[PDB]
Image: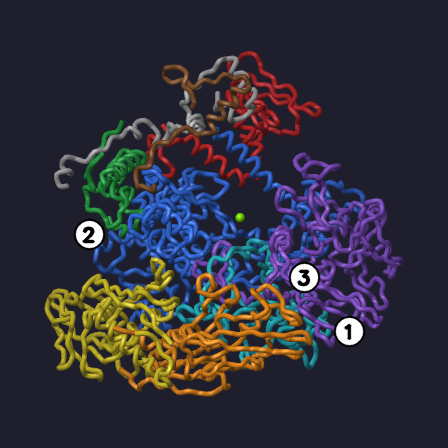
Chain colours: A cyan, C purple, D brown, E blue, F orange, G yellow, H green, I red
Amino acid sequence: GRHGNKGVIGKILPVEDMPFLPDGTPVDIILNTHGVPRRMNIGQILETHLGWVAKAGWNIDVAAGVPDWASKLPEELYSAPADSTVATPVFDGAQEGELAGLLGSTLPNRDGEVMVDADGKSTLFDGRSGEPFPYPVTVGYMYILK
Amino acid sequence: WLSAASFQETTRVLTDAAINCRSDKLNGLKENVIIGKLIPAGTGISRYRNIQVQPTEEARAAA
Amino acid sequence: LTHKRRLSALGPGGLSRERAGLEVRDVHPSHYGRMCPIETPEGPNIGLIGSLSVYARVNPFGFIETPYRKVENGVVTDQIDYLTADEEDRHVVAQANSPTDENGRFTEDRVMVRKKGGEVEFVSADQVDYMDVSPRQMVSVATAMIPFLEHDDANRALMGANMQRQAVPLVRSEAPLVGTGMELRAAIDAGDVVVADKTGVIEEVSADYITVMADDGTRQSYRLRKFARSNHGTCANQRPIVDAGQRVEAGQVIADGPCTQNGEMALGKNLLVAIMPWEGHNYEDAIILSNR
Amino acid sequence: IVKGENIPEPGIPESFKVLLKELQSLCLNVEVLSSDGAAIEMR
Amino acid sequence: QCGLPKLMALELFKPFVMKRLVDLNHAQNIKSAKRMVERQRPQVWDVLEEVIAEHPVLLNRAPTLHRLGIQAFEPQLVEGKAIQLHPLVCEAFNADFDGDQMAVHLPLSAEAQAEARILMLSSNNILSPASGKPLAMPRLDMVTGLYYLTTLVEGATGEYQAATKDAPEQGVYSSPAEAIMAMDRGALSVRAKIKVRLTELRPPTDLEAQLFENGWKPGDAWTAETTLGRVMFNELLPKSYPFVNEQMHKKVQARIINDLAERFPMIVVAQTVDKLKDAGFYWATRSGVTVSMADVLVPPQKQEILERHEAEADAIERKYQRGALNHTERNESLVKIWQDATEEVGKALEEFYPADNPIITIVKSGATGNLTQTRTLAGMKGLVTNPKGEFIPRPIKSSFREGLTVLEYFINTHGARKGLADTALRTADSGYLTRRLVD
Amino acid sequence: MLISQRPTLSEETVAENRSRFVIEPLEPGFGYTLGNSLRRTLLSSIPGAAVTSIRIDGVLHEFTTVPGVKEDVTDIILNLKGLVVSSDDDEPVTMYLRKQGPGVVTAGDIVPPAGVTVHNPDMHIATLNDKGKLEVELVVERGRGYVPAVQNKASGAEIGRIPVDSIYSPVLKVTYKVEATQRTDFDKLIIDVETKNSISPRDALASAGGTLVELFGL
Amino acid sequence: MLISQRPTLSEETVAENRSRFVIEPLEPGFGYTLGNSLRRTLLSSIPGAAVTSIRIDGVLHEFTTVPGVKEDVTDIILNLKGLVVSSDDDEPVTMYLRKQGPGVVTAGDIVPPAGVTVHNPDMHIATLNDKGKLEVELVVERGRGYVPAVQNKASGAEIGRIPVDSIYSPVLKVTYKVEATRVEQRTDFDKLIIDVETKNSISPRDALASAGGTLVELFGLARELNADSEHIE
Amino acid sequence: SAYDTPLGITNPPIDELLSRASSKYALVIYAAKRARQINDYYNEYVGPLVEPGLQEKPLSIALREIHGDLLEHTEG
Amino acid sequence: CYGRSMATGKLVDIGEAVGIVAAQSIGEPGTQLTGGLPRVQELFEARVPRNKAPIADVAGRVRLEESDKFFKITIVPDDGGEEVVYDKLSKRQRLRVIGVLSDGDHVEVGDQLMEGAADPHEV
Ligand SMILES: [Mg+2]
């Protein structure tokens, strides 16, 4: 990715057995949790969240009024459809408050159910044993280069 | 002297060696590496490399 | 695009890579807005090679200048003056983002400023002269392409810039779902995308070439690079993004280049990511992929 | 290996033979002596 | 063992297979054998597995620092062009999977193969030959996997009570196989406090004398109170080993594996660690460890703490603005004020994080990371050094969670680069020293 | 405490390409293992219904263009990947496509032989102009899973044939979920099966079970 | 449609109680797909009879103890959980164990009613201290899986009624793994290793075929929908 | 001792082999020469005193022979 | 004399080459040495220390004296023999610690008088 996170492909699994969302939507990449925290690249987790936002779309936050966090302020950004592309210029980008507010938004997969919470996490089902993974796992969309 | 030459200050070493007319016994392991001999350490030591192996007469009987 | 814009201290007429000490490799306070501090090689070229900043501009005498907006009496004008390092030490450079007031003026009681140390200081709107043209003056093009740059340590950012220029064009070339400003303007200025130099309409679109009939009555055509082998063996293939009837304007993007989609740099794909550790397969920086 | 026989005993590295030659060209007289009979010839 | 790309294996062993497929009548003469291998006709693969069997190979990764930088393994034909490296040898090779490469060497003569199997074999080299500490010991993922396995959770599902009045104890299980049937159903938690009867494991020392002392428990039954995971953990250790019943930090894991080397043959330690690996991974993924902007917590006291020292700074700076203060002392003072505050935010931060948070568990278990690292992520990165080597009295008040600022960022790289340059010349000089030590 | 009311599998309808399936009751802690056991088999072993190779008169290989066509041959092969076909098979059978003059080519323009059909003629292939002419034949084979393009050096093909990656996967996206049946709880699982229109969710789940039944033995 | 070659099912016998089973070769990824379903069918799906509730004479409001025996309340319950007897009743049946004097009680002293047969008589229950007697009633009902001790209504009116965790199924432990063959005729094919430890009621081979049938017909619900698409035999 | 079962190269265990020779280095020459000895027979001449495995490599044979105390050696 | 092999955990084998192993055991961590590699190299190369610090030449009580910019240390030997003086000690080096050396403290034949690096040749 653009944050200095690099690695070789160690394995490629049949789409059958992979962590897959409640929709039955398999994840494409599984990145290890341990390399992230110590390297100070955490920007890669942000764009992982935004990546999910930009992919699924979202809405306000209104009415009646605009919430406190949006006041500083997203302008005309209150609604974007699914798959819209985002731009956060380096030294004025989105801000932590604005992420959470967007993190809840918006259904559906197709059916009105939501696949990710306000923490940017989801319950993945192991495609191997078929049972869910005991804890909520972070999912999203990341931009990775070959 | 060829151990010292390979280490550093090669020209200084070779010139002093040729004047002192130095003879290298080739005892050290770096010397034996350069010439392709068996280093005098580990399995290259005399006691190990000269081991002689034969099956026990008891073993040959069972065949 | 970054190979041009690179500035290195080695070569004839300059110091050798081995002799120069770390004092030249360190970033100087005057590099601000001129030479990007975050971008250099990781090898033992560190600090000897750097990329020119985004708004930096070269002087007829060979000194780099950076654009500034001069402030007078707590009011930032539209006057934009390009200053060298000498004349920047002369004045007080207001911070790029300081609250703006109505028709514009200092809002915040006091102003963020850079001195001639360069030593940073906090003074009111009274004593300022110039202000920064915008954030990321110090940043280079590739650096300016890292979303959430401000959250990543300079170590991993440097690696991030270097590795963007290390990517390879995919057959499909999808653009980044979460981008930054530069993707648009870095691709057109690279020259690997086909831009129209006159307003008009498309007469023909073939995989081989694209012709446009200008309002000027003139006729311009562009032959498309197709599966051209690049220096290191990547693929330069281009594809038309326009259709026969289409109207087009001067400076628009007729065809995509190797790494571009619809005019912006696409150096990779958007992938669905799961950050869990998985059965000891993705471990110690390794990655696992969907056979998809 | 192709006949499945035992791997034979190694010989002299060619690079070493070269080193002796390069030292001779400096007017350094380098002799390889056995226990005796004195000088051995690389050939 | 190691994964060996089959194409790579074919060329490496080419003269060996050429003979084999001439022995079997696949090819009539050596010339035909050579073409058969070059064109990769499908018959050769079955033959390759034959010659490669129990025929070792040396693996090296540069730079080679200690002799452990080369180790022998048992080659396994693998699909793909990459090399499969056992996860427990990364420590010795210092092997990152960021794209490192490694060299394979084929020992030929009987002596060379003997030296590979006996001297250099992977499983016979475990402890570092410097400190004697264990190297192949689990790390990273495997830590957090076992740390999670052995940890004890107050009030988990199925917790032994124990019952009073109208009910019997309720936290007891016929066997470990029962607690599994209870765990698969929602009844039991792997981290629960239950007590169980164990026929096939060995109690500790003290509880051993009091319970048996005849005596021993080769097939015998006995009962202790432990987490279900701690049971399964001890099933990984040798049956002859006593029951540890701790939550395993890295150091605790080092203690045990260090102990296995003193009391047991190497092959035992080789296999014990293999079992720690398989278990540690399975539970590292079931551990529920991830990262999120949410799981990154910031102490609320940071604001007041920040402004608390802002006054002390501007006041001491106010004392310098008055003219009496020594300039070097005022700046020096700012170091001590801010340096001190950095600890309070560290103290405040550590106090805030719930003990089960994924970021903290990684560092607690000793798998990876520091507190100093988690102090810059949330809270404050702290003071940074100028290129001159001095300390810039301007602190970085923001953390990489909230993001730094234009000037905060320009200042950080000032020092952060000088460190990355050092790492360059630290290997150049360290290797120059090692070459003199060696000689 | 044996509770035997033999499992009941009742169908459903959601859309035409997908339909929900439900099975009740089942002993506690089943549907997950039983659901994933079907999903794993659905996403893999349902047969197809895929296109193997293609031949284009003008072009001898994948990396050239065609006069007047907007898409290069490689970007056209990518498009033809999205073809969802179905064939009674057996044995290979060639399809045919020829289009002249301006327009837009789509899967509808593909004339299938007797015994095959194209289930999404709406699909865009290539856009042609006044000079554009596209004459291409396509070979549909039968199988299951994903088979990477078989190179004609391994097969017996000549320089003209363009091998292509083949996806035989009637099924599109699959999920499931369970709801217990309080004490006495049982398990009832619902599986959500969607297909590409080459077959109905019913026939695929029948395939999976049939393929899944034959496998269990003792 | 489908033909493939070739699966086979073999078994290594670890002990009269235990057996290991391996299937070779599978088609990737079928190891993970089936094998987790097999561990379930053997564990939770196999009919067997186990103890449900027990009441001892002399234990009503007492927390834990039994004067005259070194085994306490808890130690005897888990002592009894291991009792394996196949019952033909389909309805809860109450057996009875009554013994006095100094001695060691075993599963042979309990008198099974007609239709219930104890498979492990040598089983130890309690040690009787000098001059002591023990009276216990045992509730035995058929079932499947592992049903934790039920207080429903809950234990309720019955005083001295102790519900116990019931191991219904014969197989007390099972686990599986996955390995890859082969010599590159079949490259990276899946091999499934299943580890079954069984109670003396049925042998491992009996519990495997039982799982085979209960699972096969189980999937008949789907096959009945069409039967058109198929696979190899 | 129960170490479970060694696979391939790890069999026989070093520890049980090191009781048959002075050091790891001696063990190397010990087995090494016996292997060169066996291979000759398939074309010194003696052995495989143990029952050969199917394809077993001579070096692997000589290690088993050493484990069973089937041969003696004298250090130089 | 060598003792246990850190690898085997037993008495070193007679073939072992322990010099190379020592060289590597020492140099390998050098990458982690950030009072560093310069000091280490200073020691193994036996160069006179960066800032030389004096060592007691003989046993006796110490008389301390502070000049302007300097320090004077005199050792009155228990002999009691010829007094031993250490002339100009830059106050930048301060002094070693027992706490910090003070007038009247006893000193043995090898003790270090000031914070710093004793000249190994001198010791
Ligand atoms: Mg690396």
User: Can residue E380 be seen at all in this image of the molecule?
Assistant: no
SS assignment at label 3: loop
Q: Earlier in the sequence, mark 1 or mark 3?
A: 1
Q: Are marks 1 and 3 in contact (CB under 8 Å)?
A: no
Mark 3 belongs to chain: C
Residue E377 vs E420, above or below: the answer is: below
Mark 1 belongs to chain: C
Q: Looking at the image, which is closer to me, C234 or F174? A: C234
SS assignment at label 1: strand
Q: Looking at the image, which is closer to me, F197 or C216? A: C216
Using residue E311 as the reference point, say whether residue E207 is left or right of it. left
Determine which of the numbered discs, if any, sits on residue E215 in the image: 2
Residue F76 vs H29, above or below: the answer is: below
CA separation in Å, label 3 and label 2: 85 Å
Q: Tell me, yes or no, whether dots 3 and 2 are on the same chain.
A: no
Which residue bears the numbered disc 1?
A: C201
Disc 1 under 8 Å from ligand 1? The reply is no
Q: Tell me, yes or no, whether dots 2 and 1 are on the same chain.
A: no
Determine which of the numbered discs, if any, sits on residue G164 in the image: none
Amino acid type of the residue tagged 1 in the rendering: Val
User: Can residue E393 be seen at all in this image of the molecule?
Assistant: yes
Disc 2 under 8 Å from ligand 1? The reply is no
Name the residue: 24% across, 65% down: G11
Q: Are marks 2 and 1 in contact (CB under 8 Å)?
A: no
Which residue bears the numbered disc 3?
A: C225
Residue E97 rendering spot, x and y as whole percentages: 50, 52
Q: Which label sits in the foreground, 3 or 2?
A: 3
CA separation in Å, label 2 and label 1: 98 Å
